[PDB]
Amino acid sequence: EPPLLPGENIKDMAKDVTYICPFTGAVRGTLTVTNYRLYFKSMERDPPFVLDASLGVINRVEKIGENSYGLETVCKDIRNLRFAHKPEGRTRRSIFENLMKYAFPVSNNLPLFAFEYKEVFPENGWKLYDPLLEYRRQGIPNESWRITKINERYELCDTYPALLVVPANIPDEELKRVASFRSRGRIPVLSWIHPESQATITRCSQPMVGVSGKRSKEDEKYLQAIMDSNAQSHKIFIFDARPSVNAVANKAKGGGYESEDAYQNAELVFLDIHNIHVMRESLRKLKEIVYPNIEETHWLSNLESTHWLEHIKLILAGALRIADKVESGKTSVVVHSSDGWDRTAQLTSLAMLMLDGYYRTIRGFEVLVEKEWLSFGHRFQLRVGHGDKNHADADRSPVFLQFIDCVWQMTRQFPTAFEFNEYFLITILDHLYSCLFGTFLCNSEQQRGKENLPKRTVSLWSYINSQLEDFTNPLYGSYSNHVLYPVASMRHLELWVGYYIRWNPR
Amino acid sequence: EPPLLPGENIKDMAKDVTYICPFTGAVRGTLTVTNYRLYFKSMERDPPFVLDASLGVINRVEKIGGNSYGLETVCKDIRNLRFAHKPEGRTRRSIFENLMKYAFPVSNNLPLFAFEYKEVFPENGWKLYDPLLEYRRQGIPNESWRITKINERYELCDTYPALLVVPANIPDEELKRVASFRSRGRIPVLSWIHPESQATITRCSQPMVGVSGKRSKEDEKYLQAIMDSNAQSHKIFIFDARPSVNAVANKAKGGGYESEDAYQNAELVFLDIHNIHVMRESLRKLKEIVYPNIEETHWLSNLESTHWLEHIKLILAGALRIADKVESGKTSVVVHSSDGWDRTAQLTSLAMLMLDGYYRTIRGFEVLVEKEWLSFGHRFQLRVGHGDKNHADADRSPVFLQFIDCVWQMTRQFPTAFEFNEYFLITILDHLYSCLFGTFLCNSEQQRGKENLPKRTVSLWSYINSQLEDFTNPLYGSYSNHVLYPVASMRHLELWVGYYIRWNPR
């Protein structure tokens, strides 16, 4: 039986169930389903064979010689579990239907387990990010950057946070017109500012140029304002995440990019970072060659054909170029993609980790994610698909998992630079799927507000901070050359075996 | 000008020579040729651009016409150097012909620079390996193993050492008959013995079975004697390095392997390690993709298509199986290949590094190489091709470089286990080509005797031991689980960037 959490109770049980381990072979024992997890335990071994998996990691439940009547569960953490029952046992129809029921609460009008979890913690992780204090830590407001309240009721842009930082001399009536030219109203707003130089990383969605080469004076002058806010007003850079050919296909459909005609003091650079469907396919290919068994002779070329490490390379390379342009070049940059909520989050949050050691602290990382991922409107419910049985949904993608891989890469190249360790990163990716906490539910701050998550769920980061000992890097604290420059090369980057090939007892 | 060694003098010089670096571009300065090296130096940079390359690393000197008038030199350490002079300068015909002269002393009846080198060192590295003392360190002679003097005039086997250790009850007249059945007289002689168990690693060439299934009673009974010498007289193992199909092709041609008919108490295992021409091709492919510039997008699959790491895997896997069979299985083993001097040296010396921590000490490694590579008749002159201009020779192969790569792998998987560091391994491979030292000249102990190398040349290991703290591993000394078991997997093994991709200043 499973050691139960507060709020968690057993919806089903089954004896003499066989799990077929592809490493250790067939093994028999007891399969429990709760409203949070799937537990399998076997006293036919020493040490006892244990399978402790939250329902949230389940992507599909499939019906299925020796041991060929049972259940397969495709998991979101790079494994499949498959079980066997008996033809004269008849538990399979009970266990299938209760997994199907409790694995997919959103599909079955049931509560996610985050809402039933009644554990208490010493700190409230929901009070850890204060938008106003984080800007203060950076020195905002100031003479060039003011806080507007125009979006405190989500009227300008319903997938942004309440408080937006914008250039001081641009007033609220001009922002309304700029919102009409930026896809979904996602206008350029301050992510981060350099303390010594006043150079900024701002972020937005794509400009609505379209087939006819449309322009916006106020948008153009908005970008000029960003450039004008920097002391050494050299030039402004615009990093578009997408490949050129994808940005041009966007233009055919209403979107597009900043022409050098219209944004006369701007350099546009395309970063050749592909869209969500590509990344989803990439991870799917990677899962196929890594689990259950790795074919050794074609290992390197199979890995190449997934493109997983090429995508990781490009993402960090993009972040590197942005970071270098702010730090070395003293120049302000504007980061956008199509919708400015997947690739852009990756790009700003990674550049910000390079630039500012605050975000390398456990507490500062929890802020970084809350700010740039949650507050800025990354669509986690859609991207991860919590408790929803449409496994084929085209709107699912590992964009956030890709971010955490890129961070791991940085920890390997700088093992003294982060207060957190590898286990913290894995733990984040366990709770990205688990739905134990409310942290990664909903698609915007506004939805998080309406569902009232802070009063109705526990914050992941409340748990983490009760347990800092398990997550701290012992070697931390002696990297006072405060800017990190990792090497984005196929020789330097490694496959995160720790995460993607962890289920082998070896 | 070059800072000259004792015995080294300038045969030629040339001003306003341009070296074209494929990383940093064109750079101008002074090209010296000595009787040891090629030096290029430029005061048109800081820090001054220096090219310090021994003539021994030069594989070919090519004219370029007659910056497109000059010399190309293809080097043996995974690089090419190319120079430019002037059409109205006319130094090229002087520098070409003096390189051609001094780069290829064996082709031009001239002395190798090892013979002209008159530096003195505190220790004599030629007195470091004493065959008799190393056997004593192992506990030999003893009741089961005696030292014969039958080969002190090289009469039994002219590519072996003077002193051979053989089983005590086999007398000298039976060895003569066993030499007739083992290719080139390379009879099974003791490499290493277990202190606790009396299990042995012995080594030889292939048995001369041939098309007709020939047998040798005394050979068969010789192997029985080896088995009889072990306490727990389990069974004897014979590890043939070659793939099965290569051993059968050998049998068609006079050679072959120990049949289970004739060697009734023996188990034969084939290790699927390919021959010298394959390995040469593998490194050639690897040189192509690594120098000058690496094509990043197909990096992994290009590396796979060299097979370099597959060969490294199989070699270490073979050593692993031999080591395991002695340590865990308490069983004696017999290692052979075709000639028992390339693959066998790789296999015994690597197994011996796993089994005995003495050989992991700098001093012990110098003994390991002297014993199993030099004394046992690895043909370095032919395999490396010292001062010889026949670059296409089919008898050249990186068998020893392959060994050093395998050792590097082991240092990475056990960074506290070896007293030596990466720089020591690179330094060994620098002096494998340099011909500064006498250590890697000639093809046998007998040739080394005739040419009288100990009185006429400096030992590489005399230099190393003057300079131990450049070669010492700081983390050494806390691995008292004394047997190493590396993992021979394409995930665990790495491309030795340090050695093969070192010429980039990055």
Image: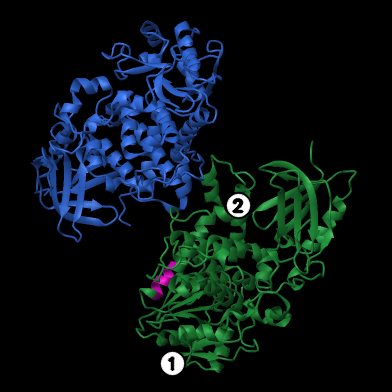
Chain colours: A green, B blue
Q: Which residue is drawn at 28% across and 52% down?
A: B22
Q: Mark 2 points at which residue?
A: A502
Q: Name the residue under label 1.
A: A143
Residue B92 seen by the camera:
no
Q: Is the magenta stretch mostly helix, strand or loop?
A: helix
Q: Helix or strand or loop: what does disc 1 sit on?
A: loop
**Left or right position of B273 against A396:** left
Horizontal and vertical percent position of residue B363: 31, 37
The quarter holding residue A422 reads: bottom right
Q: Is residue A322 magenta?
A: yes
Q: Find the magenta span and give its range.
A: A320-326
Q: Which residue is drawn at 9% across and 42% down?
A: B12
Q: Residue at x 55, y 47 (%)?
A: A302
**Callout 1, which amino acid?**
Glu
**Left or right position of B12 against A109:** left
Q: Residue at x 37, y 24 (%)?
A: B341
Q: Which of A351 and B165 is in front in this view?
A: B165
Subunit under mark 2 = A
Q: Which of marks 2 and 1 is nearer the N terminus?
A: 1
Q: Helix or strand or loop: what does disc 2 sit on?
A: loop
Subunit under mark 1 = A
What is the C-alpha distance between the residues marked 2 and 1? 51 Å
Horizontal and vertical percent position of residue B499: 34, 45
